[PDB]
Structures are given as C-alpha cells and as structure tokens.
Image (cartoon, rainbow, N blue to C red; front, side, top):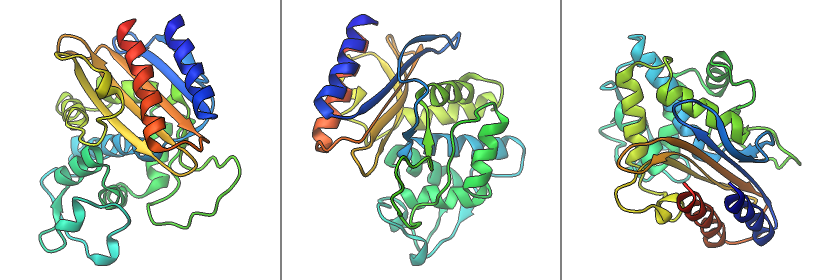
Length: 263
C-alpha cells in the first residue's frame, strides 16, 4: 500500500512522533501492510476489547453471566466514568459494563471487569495463553503514574494486537455468540468519531475501539469493510507527539482516508 505508507510516514513527520500501523486480512490473517509492526506502543483503552474477550470466555465457560449485577461505590469511581458514575445505587450488569467499557471507554467499568477476571495479571495470562506473548496489561485505572522512560507497562505491538483481535473476533477461542457480542459492542463505539469513522463511506461496516493517553498517545483498533461486512483489521497507534488531540485525530483520519481510497 504505497500511498498509505507515504501517509503513515507523513503522519510521523507531522506529529514528530512514532506511528505504528498494520492492515490484516480478516479471513486469512495475512499482513497486508505494516509500519513499525513489532515496536511497543501504549495500548491505552484499546485493551478494553481484550478485557471483554476474557470476560466472554468466562461466560462461555459458565463461570460468568452477562446478566449478573455488580454493585460498587463512590470509592470505586476513577477518572472518566461517564456511565458507571450514574449507577452507584442500582449497579450495572456485566453486559452493561462491557458496553460502557467498549463503547464509551468508561474506566471504572474496565476496573470492575478486571476484578471479575482476576486482574491485570490474569488478563495478561489469558493473552499469553492464546499465543500473544507481547501484549501486557499491568495496571488498573487509578494506580500511581510514575513516568518511566520507555515504559513497557500496558503496551502492545501493532502486529500482536491485530493478530489477537482477529483471534478474538473470528477464532474458536470464543463461542459464536460471544464473538458476535464482542464485535457488536465495537460496532456501537460512541467515542471514535474523528478517527477511522470520519473517513468511512456510507454503507461500510466498522467495529472499533479508540484509545487516548498522556505523552501524545492516541490509537484505534478496528474491523471494517465495504458493503456492511468487515473484511480487514486495522490497528494504528501513535505516541510521543506534542500535538493536540485534534492533530493526532486528523493524522489517523487521513491514514484512514488513504486506506479506504486504496482498499
């Protein structure tokens, strides 16, 4: 994808930052194109899809129920909890929590779900067990933010994340019901408008999950395709930029426009 690689490298120039990129064929798993596929980037909230994959594996095993109601309190609420902060009294079901975590990127929802699966170490063990020896979740939201240079906590690589997303959405790891639920939550994503969705022509399918973080971090994982059906996985990460979120959004959108134009 020569024109798209030109745009990915341009994004690095414009942002003064690293950009990682991969296109993966959904059906075959082949890498169609990549840039920095095996460099680490902060995952940010894109891990929330993997988290709910782990939750669904427990549901499939009969050890979790999507309808199970979880009660929590004020002290559970962390920064950016637009859905969970409304249900202190009523609580929320596991299904509602995954919807909040994926479609709104609700941070308390992610913490509550992490607790149900045994925490970050158990999520990382789940990933390791399905063949991803790279992606690691280390911290709950709200844990102390001691800046470490080249911090490897809470990171993935574009190729690892793309392969792992493909396995979750199409592999035999999850039941059909759970695969469909996971992609349905991603299709209902509400906070990724200015990224790939802004470049997407009418009639196209997209299921995605955005992320944002300090130090210029911004990213998206997606399954998308024309004619109402996904046929490709796209993963884009950037970190290090001093640019505003608008500028990072725009570079990702422009990569998306190139992706679509040269589909």
